[PDB]
Image: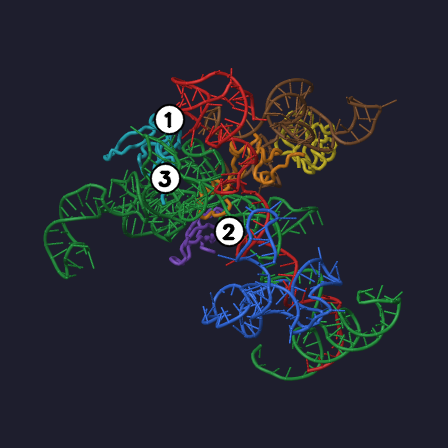
Chain colours: A orange, B purple, C cyan, D yellow, E brown, F blue, G red, H green
Amino acid sequence: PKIKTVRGAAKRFKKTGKGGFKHKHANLRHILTKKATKRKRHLRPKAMVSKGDLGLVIACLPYA
Amino acid sequence: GIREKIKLVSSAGTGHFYTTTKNKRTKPEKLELKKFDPVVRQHVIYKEAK
Amino acid sequence: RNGRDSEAKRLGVKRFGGESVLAGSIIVRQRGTKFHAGANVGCGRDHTLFAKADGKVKFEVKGPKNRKFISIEAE
Amino acid sequence: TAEIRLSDLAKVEGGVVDLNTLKAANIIGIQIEFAKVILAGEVTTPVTVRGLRVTKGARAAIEAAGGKIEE
RNA sequence: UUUUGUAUAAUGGGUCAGCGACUUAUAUUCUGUAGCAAGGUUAACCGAAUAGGGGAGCCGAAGGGAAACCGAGUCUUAACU
RNA sequence: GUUUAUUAAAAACACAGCACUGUGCAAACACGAAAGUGGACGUAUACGGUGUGACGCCUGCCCGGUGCCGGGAGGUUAAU
RNA sequence: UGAACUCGCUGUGAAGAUGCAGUGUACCCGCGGCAAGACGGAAAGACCCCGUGAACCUUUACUAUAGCUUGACACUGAACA
RNA sequence: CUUUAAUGUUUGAUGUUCUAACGUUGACCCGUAAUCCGGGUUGCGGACAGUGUCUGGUGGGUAGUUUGACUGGGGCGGUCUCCUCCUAAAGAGUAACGGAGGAGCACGAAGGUUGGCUAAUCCUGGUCGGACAUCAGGAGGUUAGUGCAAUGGCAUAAGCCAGCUUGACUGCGAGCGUGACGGCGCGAGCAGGUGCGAAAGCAGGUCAUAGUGAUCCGGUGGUUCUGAAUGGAAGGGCCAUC
């Protein structure tokens, strides 16, 4: 049987031109009054997945 | 955390708002600070609101 | 009742004298002011020392209190 | 929706391009309904596109080649 | 064999003969090799049939963005030295 | 008298007696998806459950808590 | 029952040596006895701990449910106050 | 409208009577030499009881499961995240159920800017007043102070006072530090629009280091981005936030 992609991962990473993955920072959901505006601004743009976790990601969704 | 959080609503028509904290009992008076409004790009008075 | 501790904040000097640095590089991490910023060196709200221009970092002593200053020479 | 390379744009039928027969040309797919033209280069024969979207590159390319754009 | 460490008084075996443990299917990634090459390849099925048909489809040459959409640019922003 | 057949036969279990409680008979209760059986071809001097354990002298105080029984003003409270 | 051409002592040693070091003693091989040793034989310790193991039992642990009980609707109607 | 009273209407709780549903493990007859069962006749109950669906309560009667780790065996006790110093061996880092302490906040000002000022502890004099209040002079030179434990810093003051204010602002951010990662910290400079100052300039919270919680699932506001025939909406997405 063909590999089953992890649905959770598929909703959190997209393939890019050079095979990397982009995601959204995990600190901009709630409890935002106490967070400085500078920190919130930096977390808004998407970020590339680190090399260490790249191996885990590609295994989770080998079809994208 | 006896001090609680509030929301400042821009007096202008735009719905942009800020958030902060204050002690109700010590200073139950409203806050009318003038702050920048990105939607209209002007400094306007923000009225405290729930 | 003891046994509590805080994780190390890795303070100290990051770039030493005679070392070329790029603008915005952090030279010293400190709590107070071990070193005072000189020419082309800025002091952050955390008292961190950063270079405002590209050059070699230099240490020296000035002031009546023999305090230690950090500057950048554009060379 | 799909993007049509400028290279294969002249490979559909002679020198006429239209939404129809692209599926016959098999360069987009039967299900694809919308279509756009992208700058791929290496286009020589003049072509005509009807109902497509040719933004800036292919538009200059076909116009220099001798094509035309119409809706 | 297991351990930092065993002649160990730690474990296992009385001996011989026979049997006894990294396999298979289907997907995906990488390496080697072969074919073709901006093209590559067919699946089911048809077939006096490992041939030949069948190009539905899949992968690739174009990406950016949540998306509309835009396009060798794109997003972010009122707008970017 | 009974019991751990196969390391414990006892102070354990049972016991006659005593008390509490349920049950008006299509009884309570038990076995059954149900029918139907047991209780009983009995029906309160009977039957079930529970505790105590011949007999003699007795069995004191407490109803807050947890149960059980009875009451009902007010509050709360599902489906609809 | 790994194989043995299977001594004592002191020391060393995975820390209690027939097997190592040093030293002492001992012709080869049976039989009848004793039971100190071969951490002797029998039983993958019941003790203790571990396993995000299991099984039974308990309750004012969690979530459920048989049973018991309340009401609404249905089977379920007709006349009076 | 406040305040009343006939007839008709929707009716519902309650009570009484009746029987034709239903009950009868009452009697008699028949099928039938039958304590079952069915039918008939009659009596007694009777719209109750009982059963089905829905629903509240009760429910170890029964069932499925849970009941942490560290640990100088385990249990008991204590600890679990974050901040300060020491251990830590002059970069960074560095363990122990090693030795000492704190934090889960506070502040529209205690923030920003401008202007000004400079303590502790002692000596001499002086109504109450005295060791220790306030006043004047001197010594002293940070032994003070710094919203909160500790360390480091701070006279250009980061300490104290006053004026005017909201830069505790929005979009970015070269380049760095820090971690396995998630992440966290520093940041000149650019654009827009502000505050203070004559001006150069300063201001993207607080002398710095604790004052914090990922994701999921949801709530509130904005935005035609999407909206499964089309036009809308619902629901998602994005931004802000709980």
Is there one chain holding both mark 1 and mark 2? Answer: no
| C-alpha span from label 1 to label 2 | 50 Å
Q: Which residue is mark 2?
A: B15
| Callout 3 crowding tier (Cα within 10 Å): few <14, some 14–19, many ≥20 | few
Name the N-terminal-most of marks 1 and 3. Answer: 1
Dots 2, 3 in contact, CB < 8 A? no
Observer-nearest residue: H151 or H145? H151
Dots 1, 3 in contact, CB < 8 A? no
The N terminus of chain D is located in which quarter?
top right
Numbered tag placed on residue C46 in the rendering: 3
- Total labels drawn: 3
Name which residue lies at 37% across and 30% down: C53
Element under label 3? loop
| Callout 1 crowding tier (Cα within 10 Å): few <14, some 14–19, many ≥20 | some
Displayed quadrant of residue H22: bottom right
Q: Chain of mark 2?
A: B
| C-alpha span from label 2 to label 3 | 35 Å
- Residue F54 position, x and y percent, is 55, 67
Is there one chain holding both mark 2 and mark 3? Answer: no
Q: Which residue is mark 1?
A: C20
Name which residue lies at 43% across and 51% down: B20
Mark 2 residue type: Gly
Mark 3 residue type: Asp
**For residue A5, side relative to residue E43 (left or right):** left
**For residue H145, side relative to residue A18 (left or right):** left
The C terminus of chain D is located in which quarter?
top right
